[PDB]
Image: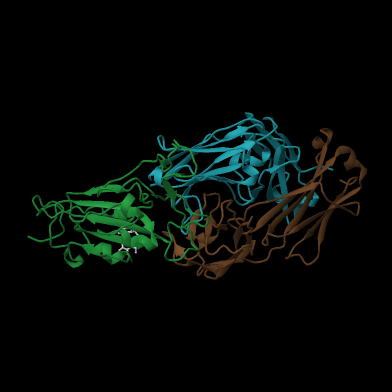
Amino acid sequence: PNITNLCPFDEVFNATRFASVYAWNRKRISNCVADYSVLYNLAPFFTFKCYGVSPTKLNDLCFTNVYADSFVIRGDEVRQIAPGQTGNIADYNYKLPDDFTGCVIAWNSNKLDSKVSGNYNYLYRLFRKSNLKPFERDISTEIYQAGNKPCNGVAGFNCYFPLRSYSFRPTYGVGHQPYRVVVLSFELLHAPATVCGPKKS
Amino acid sequence: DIQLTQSPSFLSASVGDRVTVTCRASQGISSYVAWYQQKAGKAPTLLIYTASTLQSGVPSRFSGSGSGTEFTLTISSLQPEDFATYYCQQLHSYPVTFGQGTRLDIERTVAAPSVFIFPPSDEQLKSGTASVVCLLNNFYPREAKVQWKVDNALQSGNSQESVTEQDSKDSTYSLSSTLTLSKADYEKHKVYACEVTHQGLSSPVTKSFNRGEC
Amino acid sequence: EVQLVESGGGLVQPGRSLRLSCAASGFRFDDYALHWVRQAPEKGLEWVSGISWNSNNIGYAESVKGRFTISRDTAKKSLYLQMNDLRAEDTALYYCVKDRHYDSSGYFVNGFDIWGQGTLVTVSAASTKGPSVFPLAPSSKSTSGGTAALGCLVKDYFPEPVTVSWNSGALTSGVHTFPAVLQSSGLYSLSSVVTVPSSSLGTQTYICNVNHKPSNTKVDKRVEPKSC
Ligand SMILES: *[C@@H]1O[C@H](CO)[C@@H](O[C@@H]2O[C@H](CO)[C@@H](O)[C@H](O)[C@H]2NC(C)=O)[C@H](O)[C@H]1NC(C)=O
């Protein structure tokens, strides 16, 4: 149809700072025209594995709305971001649903998020009472006490602080290097057809 | 912490040549180094970062290289606005450390400085102070040496000097020496002399006067 | 355009505090690290302080640590460097700079991109006074090749640097005014001299006009060749 203003695909993929994985951010892309060419043209990235659609033909189809997320994770565990996988971030931080129709993008950031002394701006949750229903965020910082005696906000055996801090260093191997991840989640109900890419006539 | 040294403190050059500034560190800092240019009385701006990546709006003539504990900044061609000061910066730890600074100068013809010596004025004497001024004018090499000689005895620890900026017309420099004496000390000596050594001067030339001579 | 403005500088005395203000515009304040740098006159550059994006990593120089306080406020887009226990060593020009990758240092990409014009801060144990002018009378030893050298000596003007003019600005060619220097006693002084051909000596009167704003003292002193 009509409408020509480009979607803000540069505010998310060029942002200097990415929010930590435990408290991720949610962005709405609507009322614009998408341009997926730039994504795989400019950025040298790996693992463009998308679910529910072939990466080649994202231009022809029209979509209802686009939801953009973003965070940073460890290198060896990037495979955990997929339905049916089990892991610390999958169980406690970010869980994908069984029925998913969208893509994931992951790229290395060893030249951005690496500190000689050690980065401490990125944190992940380590343990929780139960799993998480898909698309849920947590900001809780209260102590989870596994001991019978109530620690009640103190430090002691059988009690641990829920959060743990990453520490990225240039001397680490490729396995532990940080990776920036952005997931795009779609829905193909195709009633309004508002936010789809370029087509003529 | 980590100390950084600029190899050339001052380096003369002409238009269209090739120059290199060597910022040497003490420890191995990988490639966390940067370079800055400061104009005449202006806030310095960034030139290069990580010694390899041009930042923005920077002429392609500038370039950088280095590794480990050695870095070099290269200017392929010289331009009239390139005359400025250059600093190198470490970025490995947290107490950051700048180099002692490199100043660039124009290239020109050697000049023999004109030497003038002035006697203290009578109006100053009654105030309780005495001063003799040694004047150097229009010398192309910035470096020089001023030695104070009184009654055939070298003087030190009580003199100060100041150098003007390079002239925009003659491209020379001017140097003034200020020697401070008390009124009692001034009248005790007989002859006051100034020693000047310069590249364009074959032998040290002394301009002097006697206290009892007009 | 990105602009940084410094304010609050001036003259103070040892043992007293001071505050500054680095206003910022043209960029998002909450996604960039900022630093305070100082520069002594004709002494290169030197680092003072730096802060992180969320005020979590702060580093000071040894010779400066434990005396000053850096504080950033995103509500007013402001950065403040509160001062304490000043000495003469801190007299310098202060720049407020903005780092490019939201964190202090150690990362691969770092650099001071935008530098403010800075403000002058001077600390001293002395007070404003009037300058004393002693003319440099030309003599037979001050002339060579038909051209003579003459000037004026202004001394002990403390507060601010002074400006000098020759023949009410008529004589400008061949004039050299040396930069002001700090005498060991703590008072500023400089000399300004001019070279003129000896043919005009004895026929032309040269009077140097020295104007000092802080003391509101306007002194014009004649210079004539010495008569033996
Ligand atoms: C992210 O920022 C860059 C700024 O460098 C944007 O511009 C691209 O810059 C690269 C660098 O050479 C060029 O190769 C591209 O052609 C530029 N893109 C253009 C002109 O559209 C970039 O567009 C931004 N957005 C991204 C990368 O998604």
Task: Tell me what residue is drawn at x 48 percent, y 46 percent.
Answer: C52
Image-based side of B104 in relation to A57, left or right: right
Please indicate, yes or no, whether residue A108 appears anywhere in the rendered image.
no
Q: How many marks?
A: 0
Quarter of the image for the C terminus of chain A: give it: bottom left
Please identify the residue farthest to the front as the structure is shown: A148
The location of residue B85, given as percent across then percent down, is 57, 57
Task: Tell me what residue is drawn at x 46 percent, y 45 percent.
Answer: A158
Image-based side of A39 in relation to A1, left or right: right
Image-based side of C218 in relation to A96, left or right: right
Quarter of the image for the N terminus of chain A: give it: bottom left
Q: Which chain is cyan?
A: C
The location of residue B173, given as percent across then percent down, is 66, 56
The location of residue C122, given as percent across then percent down, is 62, 37
Front residue of C27 and A98: A98
Q: Which chain is green?
A: A
Front residue of A131 and B164: A131
Q: Residue B171 is drawn in which quadrant?
A: bottom right
The location of residue B92, given as percent across then percent down, is 55, 57
Front residue of C3 and C185: C3
Front residue of B207 and C15: C15
The scheme the figure's colours follow is: by chain
Image-based side of B168 in relation to C25, left or right: right
Task: Tell me what residue is drawn at x 54 percent, y 64 percent.
Answer: B30
Please indicate, yes or no, whether residue A99 appears anywhere in the rendered image.
yes
Task: Tell me what residue is drawn at x 17 percent, y 63 percent.
Answer: A53
The picture quadrant for ligand 1 comes to bottom left
Q: Is residue B116 above or below residue B77?
A: above
What hue does chain B carry in this figure? brown
